[PDB]
Amino acid sequence: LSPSARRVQGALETRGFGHLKVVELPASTRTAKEAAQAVGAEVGQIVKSLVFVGEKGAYLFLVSGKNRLDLGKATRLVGGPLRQATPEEVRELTGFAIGGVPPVGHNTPLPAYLDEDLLGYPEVWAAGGTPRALFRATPKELLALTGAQVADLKEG
Ligand SMILES: C[C@H](N)C(=O)NS(=O)(=O)OC[C@H]1O[C@@H](n2cnc3c(N)ncnc32)[C@H](O)[C@@H]1O
């Protein structure tokens, strides 16, 4: 596993979820669409870790591959103005580059929100730190791993 992918594996291990495995695939997983095709999953099963900057800090939004994050909803949930983090901010905050941003192992653990639609799948796939890394897990484990709060995040 490449460094960033290893960093994520390490985080899964340190959390007590060592049985979850990061895989650096022979096919791209840069976008939810590609990720789903790479593992034969439904796009909705892909977890997009989206980082947004607020006035007093950063926030992690775990969105289903089939939904579009509603900034209006996110803003209300946090209770303050929010904005999509620039590629640069993603790197400084999380330590990973967009297209590979994982839900764990960041430079600072960010308060998180989980797209309630992810609770509809028995298993989901999140990014493992690179545009080729992914690790499968149950929504429950993703919740335990991030301590995120379930929420209505989609524009739809
Ligand atoms: C799972 C897959 N590896 C992945 O990383 N999916 S992702 O949705 O989290 O990554 C793509 C998302 O990053 C964000 N993004 C893409 N380009 C961006 C840019 N130029 N600036 C800020 N955010 C961007 C958008 O939400 C885009 O949908």
Image (tube, grey):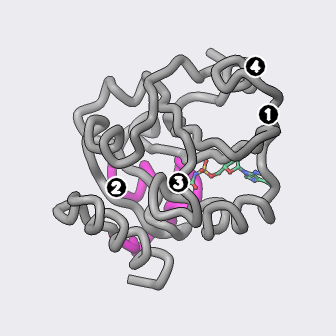
Q: Secondary structure at mark 4?
A: helix
Give 149 or 156, whichever is nearer the viewer: 149
Q: Assess mark 1: CB under 8 A from ligand 1?
A: no
In this orientation, which residue lies closer to the viewer: 50 or 66? Answer: 50
Rendered-image quadrant of the N terminus: bottom left
- x and y percent of residue 14 in the render? 29, 67
Q: CA distance from mark 1 to mark 2?
A: 33 Å
Q: Which residues are magenta?
A: 23-40
Residue 75 location (% of width, % of height): 73, 24
- Residue 109 is tagged as 3
- The residue shown at (82%, 28%) is 81
Q: Earlier in the sequence, mark 1 or mark 3?
A: 1
Label 3 packing within 10 angstroms: few (<14), some (14-19), many (20+): some
Where disc 3 sits, the SS reads: loop
Identify residue type, mark 3. Answer: Pro
Q: Which residue is mark 4?
A: 72
**Lower sequence index among marks 1 and 2:** 2
Contact between labelled residues 2 and 1, with CB atoms less than 8 Å apart: no
Q: Which mark is residue 39?
A: 2
For the C terminus, give its image quadrant.
Answer: top right
* Residue found at the far bottom of this picture: 2
Give percent across and percent down for residue 123: 26, 40
Mark 4 or mark 3: which is in front? 3
Q: Please tell me whether mark 1 sits on a helix, a strand or a loop.
A: strand
Left or right for 154, reference 76: left
Pointer 1 and pointer 4: residues touching (CB < 8 Å)? no
**Disc 2: residue Cβ within 8 A of ligand 1's nearest atom:** no
**Mark sitting on residue 82:** 1
Please state which amino acid type lies under the numbered disc 1: Leu
Q: Distance of mark 2 from mark 3, alpha carbons? A: 27 Å
